[PDB]
Image 1 (cartoon, rainbow over the protein chains, first blue to last red):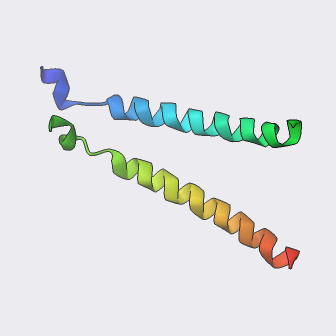
Image 2 (tube, rainbow over the protein chains, first blue to last red; image 1 turned 60 degrees about the vertical axis):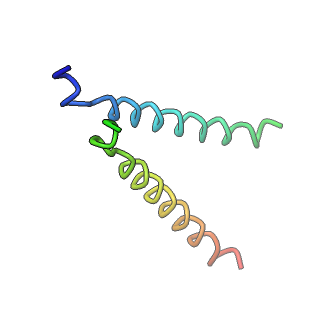
Amino acid sequence: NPYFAAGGGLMILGTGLAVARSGIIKASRVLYRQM
Amino acid sequence: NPYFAAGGGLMILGTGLAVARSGIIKASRVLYRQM
């Protein structure tokens, strides 16, 4: 399809993994000091 | 594969090395004043 030329889904994946990294970092920041 | 046209992994590597640089800078900021 002509939409394949854009191929902007990698931006979505990058935002998703960045948010996941931030959330996991905050969790581990709480996990160590919780147990 | 058609996914090679995008080639967005360099963004992932850049984010990883930037985070590593920040973490190492903070560590050295603690390492000098710890020992």
